[PDB]
Structure formats: structure tokens, C-alpha cells
Amino acid sequence: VLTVSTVNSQDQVTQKPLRDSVKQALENYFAQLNGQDVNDLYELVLAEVEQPLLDMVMQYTRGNQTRAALMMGINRGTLRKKLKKYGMN
Amino acid sequence: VLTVSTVNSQDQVTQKPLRDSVKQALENYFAQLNGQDVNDLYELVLAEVEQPLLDMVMQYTRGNQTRAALMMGINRGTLRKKLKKYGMN
Image: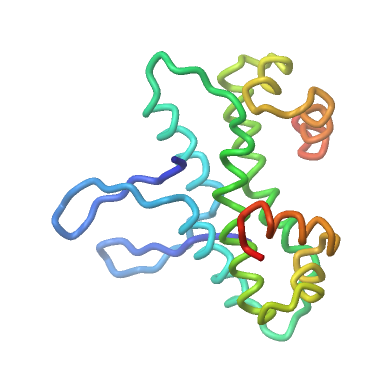
């Protein structure tokens, strides 16, 4: 589940699991620090992951929150809270 | 912030934002589905993203939970709960 697709030069399509991009993304972040200290990292990662998720869902549910919240599997309230967090409603 | 590096058609290394690999990863998931209900999407995506983050941070804090939770910016308790969730401690 949850995998981006890629090709090689041989024109074969292969599925690279999403967690691999996340590890690279975290490590490229650290690579871009020197001296700096790392805090509130969880908030960083979640913004990048929740915005596309909420956007993607709202698209398929056609803006219906009760169905968005049912597909995602969280409370209507949490949903309402997060959409605000990202200025999405 | 939070970006994977790729090489492109001009032959240059370039940084694609992690959010884009998430959107792709979600849409390929629906792709593979045909006529199946999807209830627990947020839990899905969150497993894929947390396991690499926890793992990466524990690497850097050398097993130190107090330093792990401070780096991530979550509560010692939360941290402790998530590690259990993922059979990581």
C-alpha cells in the first residue's frame, strides 16, 4: 500500500514505497542544517503529509465533510479542526 | 522543507517536495482499488509516515527517548505510545 511508481532505463515500471521518500526527505533536511538544532520535527512532517491527504480526499468526496471524515476515519470535529489548520475551509 | 532529490532532463539534481510524493502515493492507492470501501485512510497514511520518522530520530538520539520526544516536539507519553503502536520499544 502507499507507493509511488518509477521507471528504469529499461522502460519497466516499478513501485517504490512511500516510506522510502519520507526517509530521504528527512535525511535531506538534516543535510541542509549545520549548527542548527532540530525541534518540532513532527509538526514539520505532518504538514507535508496532511495537506495533500485532505486535499485529495475533499476532491473525491466533492467537498462533503461527512464523507471525507468517514473515508479518512476520523471525527468530523478533528476534520473540521485540521481543515482550519491548513486554511482549507 | 522536506524534499526528495531527483535528476532531470537537463541532467540536473533538483528537489521535488515530499507532499507531491504523498499525493501520488494516495492516488495510486485508489487506482488499485475497484469497488472496495475505504474507511481507515488517515491511519493508513500515518503508519507510512511515522515509522520512518520515529526510526530516523531514535537513530540520531541514540535510543534516548527524552531526546527523541524533545526533537520531535511531542510529549514523552505520546512518544511512548507511538513506539508501542509500531512495536518499536
